Amino acid sequence: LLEKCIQSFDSAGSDHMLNMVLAMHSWVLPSADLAARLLTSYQKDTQELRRLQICHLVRYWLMRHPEVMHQDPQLEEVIGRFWATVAREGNSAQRRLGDSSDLLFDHLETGELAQHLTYLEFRSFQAITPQDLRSYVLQGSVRGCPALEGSVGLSNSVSRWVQVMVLSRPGPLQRAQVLDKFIHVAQRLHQLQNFNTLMAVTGGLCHSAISRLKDSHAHLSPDSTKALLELTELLASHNNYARYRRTWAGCAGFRLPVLGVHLKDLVSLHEAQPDRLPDGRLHLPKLNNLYLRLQELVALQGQHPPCSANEDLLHLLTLSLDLFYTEDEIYELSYARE
Amino acid sequence: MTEYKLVVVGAGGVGKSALTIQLIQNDPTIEDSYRKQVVIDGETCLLDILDTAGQEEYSAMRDQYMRTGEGFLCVFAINNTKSFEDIHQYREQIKRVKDSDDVPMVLVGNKARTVESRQAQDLARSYGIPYIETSAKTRQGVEDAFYTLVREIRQH
Image (cartoon, rainbow over all chains, first blue to last red; front, side):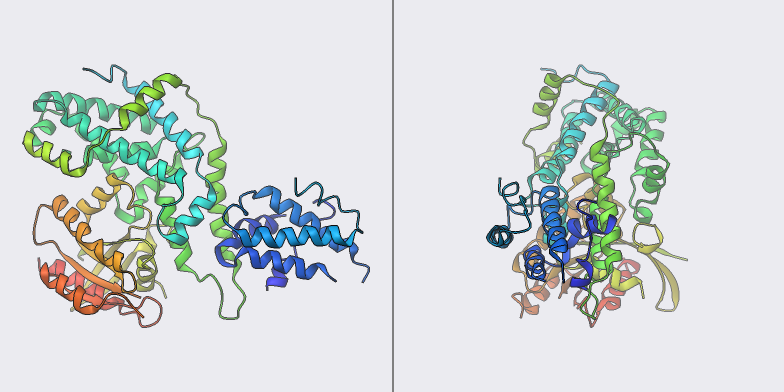
């Protein structure tokens, strides 16, 4: 099927399959072997035409995924041999070679905090590379892939900041006021359809070190408690987040900070169906589902936020998030307050 | 009937998603695919299983599935010593979120090998929880593990 799948055509410049193969082949079949397949299939009745088609495919796929050569000396070697071979023929007038080898902290308000947090979350999210997702699915750990590491650390720092911001207040009433404010922030994040930061803030509210403060939830407004319950119901684990998914489907326009559950889904689709069939050929529908699920995320990386923000104020908030507290000190403080 | 909330905890790359899938089907996006209606010890029951593939990194989601979760599969791979070393902090975090020394869970080895079953059983006995080993690919000693956790919940 390898020779059967590579047969994607370009009429001197012209598909969906082609895009899928070039983006998703690295999941199953290593790319160096694919490049060797192209070089070997190069040498073949009046078919300098298809040799040009091959050169155009190489140029296309190297230009679309320019990252296929940072971590892969083997692919670099084989494509260098490929361009040297075409340059060493001399025919076909392929200039593809010469064109190829070249103290108070938050005086803000609810909506403004939500919008600045959303702007940070979107800027850190937008830096995530699909090959980072590949490395997450295969390797099993984000590690060695900085963009999503920064995204997950962003969410963790948001939750930590929420917890320590609630616990930094003496008395259950002061903490309850902080809880009202964060519930309103979560409401505005739901209105803005930023569900990732919504998860971070809600879990900071629903964290065990915070949920145990009964006096504070006693002073918490009944409407606030109702909203918090509805939000926890929204981000709950039941039925692989079916409520979250119903909303996510029912959202539109700029709904698109997403949750790491997509990561989950990817991993699921990776192990549900096999990479390769026992025939020796690999079955594409798995890679098609994966490819469209990733292109969804890329398309989300494309759009623009509706709200704007102050870059320096973003810097101040980012500096507010980078504290150094562990679950140990957080629990020690929550215990010290009840 | 009775509904049991199961959570599959462990490091990535051990196959916990592959095992969880091998339990149910023979499309995870929908809510159906992580729910299995099966009959245990005479009576029917509903297994609401939750894999923790991408959710480990987020502390908030970690606490949500630990607070909602009723039973836990602390999974590791027999060919990875570090995967076996992480189970300790898994158990300690679960203890802090549940505030109890008697938490329903079951230790599972999965997939030569660098962990010997004697070590894992010594740890499982060290904190009074059953221990089973599986092969997600062929033998699928899976129903025994999940149903062991179900019985651990029922007998809490």
